[PDB]
RNA sequence: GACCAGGAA
């Protein structure tokens, strides 16, 4: 029912090799130097150039078919500008207090290096991604 | 003015260039399909042949006879022979044409659609007269004769639609375009160097604003506005192909409700 | 001819109109069949016993994975293959309107619209995603193609988890009839039955999607761009020089024979090898130049038809023609054709075809190509007969 | 070799093939014409007796 | 019909291959495929 | 064609000159100066395989005659006329071809056997085989209802009367994936 | 200039007059 | 073998236009790409229909009974 | 020879009905109508219009084989709302739209002088 | 347009298909391979024209 | 079959409304698969098309004679002069939906030939029928009603 | 029905 991870990042690079509409993104955290990010992103839908400072959330909610409209009358867990829904598919222990999680948003991939949100990121198909700014 | 709109860009006996606006593409397309496929027309559908001394075979000629456009204006007040009550056909459901031709001249003698003549009773409705757009008013050159070449046959035209045979198609090609600056990205341009340089702009580029590159892609967008052009073979006047198609389609969508109701 | 078990298989009848036997496109290959006019026999059992034998032993689904090579002997092919690639790129997204049709089209579908990979701005699905609606659960498959991370950077390999595509493009290596097979697995894992259902499902979706994407190919796709063209011409040019030299060398008696070869046998080995290096380089030159959007390269990448060498001779250079291994003979005294001077050991004289198929062959090139070609047709019709008796 | 190890046979048919994206893998489209020629000998039984009479 | 009247048969050390000498006299391409490949030539 | 150095005025050159070409087509428009004309004036000559051995042939003439004392990218790559020793010229390379083959368009752009097929398949095609078809009682024959001459043609078609008695129709063709049908 | 060099297009004219004389079945007849 | 009524592809009426196209040629000494266009044949399916037609009937005619 | 009659594309076969409605077993409040003697013209058009109905949760159609003029249409709606009525409403919508379209073209065409 | 060059025998049109053969009165030498007592042979197939 | 050894049977017929269309209202008579071309390398087909498209537009006979100075480049230039894109592609719209095809199609005239092999002359079925006398096995050949 | 001959995926 609740959020799983939260931080602001800043992009080191935007790569669109061979892809008309998608770019893989490279950011690191403002708070932790320990905290990196790699993210395939739909630029057509939400464009990006480097140095952009993006906020990034996770959360498991806000099972069953997907209902489209009426969302005027709905609790959009978005105060955001772009939201995906993917699957956790690798928990890579990279030494130390250091860990990485791997997500797949129907092909759009994501890798997140960090430490401390052990008590958070489960191997859940239920994993929504969120971006503002 | 109401719902979907029209602006007409050019018009003739046999060509309506216009713009559909404020519509589902699916709708615009359905009209296109209907206009081609489902508007009723009269065309010769049976040919009994009494004599043929031509270089052309009986059925070879028969086939051509199906392709001559016939006056189909008041076609809606002719019955489908299938539903008419006579065994075979009558005056209520069919037009009877007759063709007699003989090589009188030494020079080659020509059999044109003008040489058809309606034997059946028209009950005074616009029907069966072969369409002639011809400059010298001869219509389709059906066949050629030499001397003892005689052609004597009889035609029964019936009501029908393109779905059953194309001979009943009131319209020829129908030009249909939208979003001439690919702003919906509904197509991805093949190119060697410059998608812009290799691909020619459409006439309709003039009728929409160029996209201007300093712009984020509009995913919200959706195809309304459609540049069409209808061309009539002549069996029905262009404007009517549009209308009757609109009407024909509607009648369909209606019959659905109607069955929904006997349900 | 019927050289396989698989060359006669039991099918379910579906009485239909028109005068052709119609069959599923994927069972095309174990029969060896193409619709360029080939007829097929159908026998009908008469006993309760014999139909049993058919449905229980030699039904198409059973014959999928095959003992000829411990792998599946049919897989996704042609349009459906060419399309399944295009469908599953990262690039490829699908609007709600369409998605709904693609789902319904899958005749099994739990009636559950899966959550779009992108929920706003504007909900989009991805090819990967809705394709997986066809792949059943518990179908677990993983392959690494060269340079694959778990964060597959190039959409390489294949990561399918519980019948969900996680990354990588679906194509021949996956959805074809490979050992690693998406097919090999589904059969061995779910049933002959489930797998045969899979074929159907995959094609209904892909074909549908491909119907509305469209796919084509034209002369445009054989055009090697300006610089890459010129650059090919020099690749050939320089190797023509490489030959001219080894020729001069062997004309002054400087050249030394290799062990076992004539002074001459040795010379030709270099020439033939120089001219094939030439062609092959010019080939790779073009292949690299061709954009991802090039339809021919697209067919090659899916593995739906064609290969490097086809691109090579269409775009770059046809290459050296050969009869009986050696280059072209002197059928005429000391020359290949009466349009040449004598003792001409050059590439032009002995049947190197400098030109691409796009540029078109010279009349000499044409005739030598012809000579080589005829040798082909013969040892085809030969290896046919010899193959037959062998099999018997 | 040609009369015993092989034979021409009854209840058989042949015609041009074409492929179908809409058939299932393990079926084959048979022309109505051939369906009407080709026969299966079915034994009258209480299970089929009415259906069988219907076809006859 | 034409091509049938410019047709050559060649009964029965290597006849089937397209020879150099055949230049300009016989078609490099127009031959039957199979039992009579290169054995039936066309002028 | 016969070539001799036979020119006070310059190098080696074909006996046949543009004057004969005039004189030739003069007689063409008249539907005197026949083929047999070229043959007794000795501008042209018959060569079997044996005699072929001992000559040297230029492919094109004009191209393979005057020396040299920019180049098209798109075009193919032709060799040269480095030889001075020419005896004869090819009348036109396209005549190494047979009848069937002479209908194949751009066949010099095809994989070699793709030609060998069509130059057998076209003999299983359909069209108007003779204009007297109506009066002949051949056991089996097919005529095309509306034959068309082809939009793309061979210069050699002229002589085969292919334009006047065709084999097919010009179909508006799309190379596309559609229904997978 | 009725003794000019001959162009490539000109060869066809000759080829034309060949078939005027021989026709396509020269051999079978002769 | 005589002009098609109606172009295969689009269906535009074409059989009336034959003698005109022949006259736009002989008498007017127009070339084909214009003669066709003068007859309002524009979509090239209709162009090919006339431009590539071989009117054999005129030969068939020359035989007798 | 094995070609069906061409009118079979539109003339209802004897003892056939335009609509047959059966309910989707796989999911709640959803239903599958088969349109006999019909094709894309009607199918795409109705699908298109149900996609405007806010209370429609799902809409698709398919011509399962091209040999046969017919199509299945699947409709799911928010509960209470009956897909049958959903179809009803969508239909009139199309009609009214075409009504304007007719009226409007006529009205413009009246103004031409050619 | 008929080009002739055929025969009409009992109604059906017959074509005489050209026959290829080695020319005669011609001198040719061949190597007679390994297992032979002969090593080279000069043949001439000779005949009255 | 085209003149490039591209034999095909029909697989289905579609009426105009189902056929993909160029905005110009044009529609194919015939749709061949793209997978014909690469393994067969029958480039001449493609050129025949590009050339024939010009010829139809220009009403000038297309020379596809063998060894000549005609280049695909040359042809492409003319075709662009005529307004269609240089390589004979053309945007096409789906017949069922009216939506554009995401791909552009190679599209143009190409001489095709009707071949003497027609299916209703081929199709054959038997289930009990005339038997040989000597062997008492089924007789041979469609004609004779064989097995 | 023997037998010969010619041509096809
Ligand atoms: Mg085959
Ligand atoms: Zn009546
Ligand atoms: Zn047309």
Image: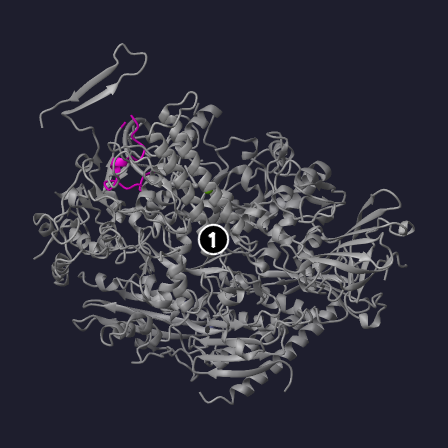
User: Looking at the image, which is closer to me, A13 or H1?
Assistant: A13
* Quarter assignment of residue F130: bottom left
- Asked if residue C257 is among those painted magenta in the image, a careful observer would answer no
Q: Which residue is mark 1?
A: C224
The N terminus of chain D lies in quadrant: top left
* Vertical position of residue I97 compared to residue B162: above or below: below
Helix, strand or loop status at disc 1: loop
Task: Look at 65% across and 47% down and name the residue there.
Answer: C170
Residue C267: name its quadrant. Answer: top left
Give the colour scheme of this rendering: one colour
Q: From where the camera sits, is residue I64 visible?
A: no
Q: Residues within 10 Å of mark 1 (few under 14, many from 20)?
A: many
Query: What residue is shown at x 49% (from left), y 49% (from top)?
Result: C286
Q: Is residue I25 left or right of residue F131?
A: right
Instruction: Report the magenta stretch's main SS.
Output: loop
The quarter of the picture where residue L7 lies is top left
Q: Which residue is most to the top?
A: J37
Where residue K116 sits in the image (x, y, percent)?
Answer: 36, 48
Given residues J37 and H51, the one toward you in this image is J37
Position in image of residue B192 (x %, y %): 50, 59
Provide the residue span drawn in magenta.
Answer: E12-32
In percent of width and height, residue C202 lies at 65, 49
On what subunit does the disc labeled 1 rest?
C
At horizontal 52% and vertical 76% (from top left) the residue drawn is B204
Q: Is residue E16 magenta?
A: yes
Task: Evaluate whether residue F99 shows in this view.
Answer: yes
Q: Nearer the viewer, residue C344 or C147?
A: C344
């Amino acid at each position: 029912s609740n959020t799983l991870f939260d931080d602001i990042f800043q992009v080191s690079e935007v790569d669109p090799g061979r892809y008309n509409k998608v770019c893989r993104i490279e950011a690191a955290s403002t708070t932790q130097d320990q905290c990196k990010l790699t993210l395939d992103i739909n630029v057509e839908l939400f464009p990006v150039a480097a140095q952009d400072s993006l906020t990034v959330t996770i959360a498991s909610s806000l099972t069953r078919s997907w209902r489209p409209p009426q969302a005027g009358d709905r609790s959009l867990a978005d105060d955001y500008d772009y939201v995906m829904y993917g699957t956790a598919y690798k928990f890579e222990e990279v030494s130390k207090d250091l860990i990485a999680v791997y997500y797949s948003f129907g092909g759009l991939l994501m890798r997140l290096e960090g430490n401390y949100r052990n008590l958070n990121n489960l191997k859940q198909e239920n994993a929504y991604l969120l971006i503002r700014r | 003015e109401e719902g979907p709109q029209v602006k007409i860009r050019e018009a003739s006996k046999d060509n309506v260039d216009f713009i559909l606006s404020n519509v589902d593409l699916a709708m615009a397309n359905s009209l296109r399909r209907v206009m081609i496929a489902e508007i009723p027309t009269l065309a010769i559908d049976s040919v009994e042949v009494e004599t043929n001394t031509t270089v052309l075979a009986d059925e070879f000629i028969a086939h051509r006879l199906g392709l001559i456009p016939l006056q189909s204006m008041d076609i809606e007040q002719l019955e489908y022979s299938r539903d008419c009550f006579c065994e075979d056909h009558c005056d209520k459901c069919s037009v009877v044409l007759t063709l007699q031709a003989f090589g009188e001249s030494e020079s080659t003698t020509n059999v044109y659609s003008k040489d058809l003549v309606i034997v059946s009773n028209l009950m005074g409705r616009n029907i069966g007269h072969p369409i002639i757009q011809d400059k010298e008013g001869n219509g389709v050159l059906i066949c050629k004769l030499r001397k003892g070449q005689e052609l004597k046959l009889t035609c029964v035209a019936k009501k029908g639609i393109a779905k059953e045979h194309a001979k009943w198609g009131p319209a020829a090609a129908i030009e249909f375009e939208y979003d001439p600056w690919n702003k919906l990205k509904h197509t991805d341009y093949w190119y060697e160097q410059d998608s812009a340089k290799e691909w020619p702009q459409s006439k309709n580029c003039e009728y929409e604003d160029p996209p201007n590159e300093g712009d984020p892609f509009d995913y919200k967008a959706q195809a309304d506005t459609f540049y069409m052009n209808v061309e009539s073979v002549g069996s029905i006047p262009v404007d009517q192909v549009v209308v009757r198609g609109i009407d024909t389609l509607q009648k369909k969508v209606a019959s659905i409700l109607l069955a929904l109701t006997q349900m | 001819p019927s050289l396989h078990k698989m060359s006669m298989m039991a099918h379910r009848v579906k009485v239909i109109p028109y005068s052709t036997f119609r069959l599923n496109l994927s069972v095309t290959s174990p029969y060896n069949a193409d619709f360029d006019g080939d007829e097929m026999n159908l026998h009908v059992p008469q006993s309760e016993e014999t139909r049993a034998e058919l449905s229980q032993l030699c039904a198409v689904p059973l014959q999928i994975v095959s003992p000829q090579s411990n792998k599946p002997c049919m897989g996704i092919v042609q349009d459906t293959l060419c399309g399944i690639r295009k469908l599953t790129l990262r690039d490829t997204f699908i609007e709600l309107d369409q998605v709904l049709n693609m789902l319904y089209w899958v005749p099994d579908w739990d009636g559950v619209i899966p959550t779009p990979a992108i929920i706003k701005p504007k909900p989009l699905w991805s090819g990967k995603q809705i394709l997986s609606v066809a792949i059943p659960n518990g179908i677990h498959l993983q392959r690494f193609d060269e340079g694959t991370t778990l964060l597959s950077p190039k959409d390489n390999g294949m990561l399918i988890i519980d019948g969900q595509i996680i990354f990588g493009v679906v194509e021949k290596k996956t959805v074809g009839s490979s050992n690693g097979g998406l097919i090999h697995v589904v059969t061995r894992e779910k049933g002959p039955q489930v797998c045969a259902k899979l074929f159907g499902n995959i094609q209904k979706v892909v074909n549908f999607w491909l119907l509305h994407n469209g796919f084509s190919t034209g002369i445009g796709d054989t055009i090697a761009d300006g610089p890459t063209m010129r650059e090919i011409t020099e690749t050939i040019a320089e190797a023509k020089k490489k030959v001219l030299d080894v020729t001069k060398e062997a004309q002054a008696n400087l050249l030394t024979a290799k062990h076992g070869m004539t002074l001459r046998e040795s010379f030709e080995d270099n020439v033939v090898r120089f001219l094939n290096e030439a062609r092959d380089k010019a080939g790779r030159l073009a292949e690299v130049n061709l954009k991802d959007l090039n339809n021919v390269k697209q067919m090659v990448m899916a593995g739906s038809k064609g290969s490097f060498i086809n691109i090579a001779q269409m775009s770059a250079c046809v290459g050296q023609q050969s009869v009986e291994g050696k280059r072209i003979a002197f059928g005429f005294v000391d020359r290949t054709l009466p349009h040449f001077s004598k003792d001409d050991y050059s590439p032009e004289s002995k049947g190197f075809v400098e030109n691409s198929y796009l540029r078109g062959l010279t009349p000499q090139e044409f005739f030598f190509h012809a000579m080589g070609g005829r040798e082909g047709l013969i040892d085809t019709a030969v290896k046919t007969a010899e193959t037959g008796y062998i099999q018997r | 070799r040609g009369n015993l190890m092989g034979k021409r046979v009854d209840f058989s048919a042949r015609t041009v093939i074409s492929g179908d994206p809409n058939l299932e893998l393990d079926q084959v489209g048979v022309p109505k014409s051939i369906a009407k020629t080709l026969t299966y000998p079915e034994v009258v039984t209480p299970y089929n007796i009415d259906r069988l009479t219907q076809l006859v | 019909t034409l091509s049938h009247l410019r047709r050559t048969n060649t009964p029965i050390a290597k006849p089937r291959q397209l020879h150099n000498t055949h230049w300009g006299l016989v078609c490099p391409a127009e031959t039957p495929e199979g039992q009579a490949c290169g054995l039936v030539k066309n002028l | 064609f016969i070539v001799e150095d036979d020119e006070s005025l310059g190098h080696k050159e074909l006996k046949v000159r543009k004057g004969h070409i005039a004189k030739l087509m003069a007689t063409e428009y008249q539907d005197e100066y026949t083929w047999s004309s070229l043959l007794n004036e000795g501008l042209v000559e018959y060569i079997d395989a044996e005699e072929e051995e001992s000559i040297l042939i230029a492919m094109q003439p004009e191209d393979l005659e005057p020396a040299e004392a920019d180049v098209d990218p798109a075009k193919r790559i032709r060799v040269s006329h480095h030889a001075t020793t020419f005896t004869h010229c090819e009348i036109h390379p396209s005549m190494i071809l047979g009848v069937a083959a002479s209908i194949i368009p751009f066949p010099d752009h095809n994989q070699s056997p793709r030609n060998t097929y069509q130059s057998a398949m076209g003999k299983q095609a359909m069209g108007v085989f003779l204009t007297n078809y109506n009066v002949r009682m051949d056991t089996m024959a097919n005529i095309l209802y509306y034959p068309q001459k082809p939009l793309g043609t061979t210069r050699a078609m002229e002589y085969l009367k292919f334009r006047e008695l065709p084999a097919g129709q010009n179909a508006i063709v799309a190379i596309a994936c559609y229904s997978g049908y | 200039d009725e003794s000019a060099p001959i162009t490539a297009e000109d060869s066809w004219a000759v080829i034309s007059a060949f078939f005027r004389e021989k026709g396509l079945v020269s051999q079978q007849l002769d | 073998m005589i002009v098609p009524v109606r172009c295969f592809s689009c269906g535009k009426v074409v059989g009336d236009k034959w003698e005109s196209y022949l006259n736009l040629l002989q008498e007017d000494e127009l070339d084909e790409g214009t003669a066709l266009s003068r007859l309002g044949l524009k979509r090239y399916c209709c162009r090919r229909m006339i431009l590539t037609h071989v009117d054999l009937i005129e030969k068939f005619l020359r035989y007798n009974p | 020879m094995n070609a069906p009659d061409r009118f079979e594309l539109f003339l209802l076969g004897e003892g056939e009905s335009k609509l047959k409605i059966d309910p989707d077993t796989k999911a709640p409040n959803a239903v599958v109508i088969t349109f006999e003697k019909e094709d894309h013209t009607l199918g795409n058009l109705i699908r298109a219009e149900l996609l405007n109905d806010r209370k429609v949760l799902f809409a698709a159609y398919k011509v399962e084989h091209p040999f046969f003029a017919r199509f299945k249409l699947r409709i799911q709606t928010t509960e209470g709302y009956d897909p049958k009525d959903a179809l009803k409403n969508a239909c009139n919508s199309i009609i009214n739209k075409l009504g304007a379209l007719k009226t409007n073209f006529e009205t413009e065409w009246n103004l031409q002088t050619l | 347009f008929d080009m002739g060059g055929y025969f009409i025998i009992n109604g059906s049109e017959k074509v005489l298909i050209a026959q290829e053969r080695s020319a005669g009165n011609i001198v040719q030498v061949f190597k007679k391979a390994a297992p032979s007592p002969i090593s080279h042979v000069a043949e001439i197939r000779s005949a009255l024209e | 079959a085209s003149r490039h050894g591209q034999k095909g049977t029909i697989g289905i017929t579609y009426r105009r409304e189902d056929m993909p269309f160029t905005a110009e209202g044009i529609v194919p008579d015939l749709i061949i698969n793209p997978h014909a071309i690469p393994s067969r390398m029958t480039v001449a087909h493609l050129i025949e098309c590009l050339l024939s498209k010009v010829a139809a537009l220009s009403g000038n006979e297309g020379d596809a004679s063998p060894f000549t100075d005609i280049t695909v480049e040359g042809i492409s230039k003319l075709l662009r002069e005529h307004g269609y894109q240089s390589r004979g592609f053309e945007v096409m719209y789906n017949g069922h939906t009216g939506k554009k095809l995401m791909a552009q199609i190679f599209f143009g005239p190409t001489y095709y030939q009707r071949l003497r092999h027609m299916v209703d002359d081929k199709i054959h079925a038997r289930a009990r029928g005339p038997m040989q006398v000597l062997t008492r096995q089924p007789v041979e050949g469609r004609s004779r009603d064989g097995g």
